[PDB]
Length: 128
Ligand SMILES: COc1cc2cc(OC)c1OCCCOC/C=C/COC(=O)[C@@H]1CCCCN1C(=O)[C@H]2C1CCCCC1
Image 1 (cartoon, rainbow, N blue to C red):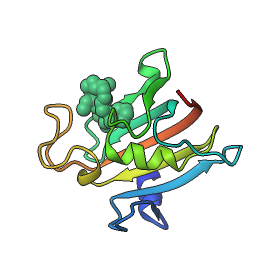
Image 2: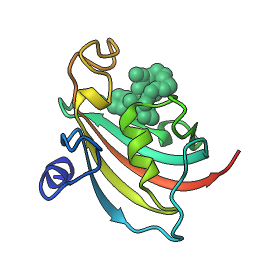
Image 3: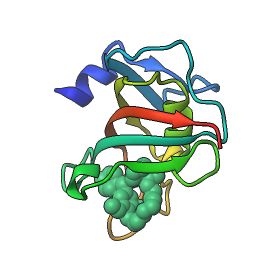
Image 4: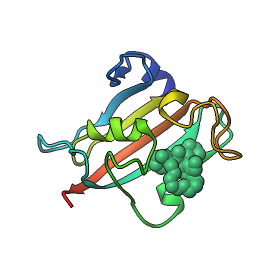
């Protein structure tokens, strides 16, 4: 399902065009403005390893996930991906290890050389 559809006609949003981060918009946002680097960004997400063994949701807590875009608080794929989103957008991203946790991984939660999948809802973003 959702990951497979992202592989299939998945929009490659890397600069190098190496298919490291593929995207589909599933619910369209409003406003023309995507976040610039530095913006304080508020999201809900669901995430999983493609190996199917771990799943993580912002809802597993009772709060949005907040982070500063482009300030290395998240994996490179998030900085690239959420910079393409509009307020109120829901998107799916499929991510190769290079744009996530690489060969080292982040044990034991993230194995070596893992591919990741996320659904992200962009709630809001303000300047700082
Ligand atoms: C690698 O560590 C984790 C990764 C994710 C969630 C974690 O805790 C809930 C988590 O545990 C340690 C606490 C880390 O919290 C700060 C940030 C971690 C970096 O996370 C990320 O960049 C991405 C994007 C933003 C949401 C979290 N996230 C993760 O990679 C998640 C994992 C969790 C395992 C399934 C795939 C998603």
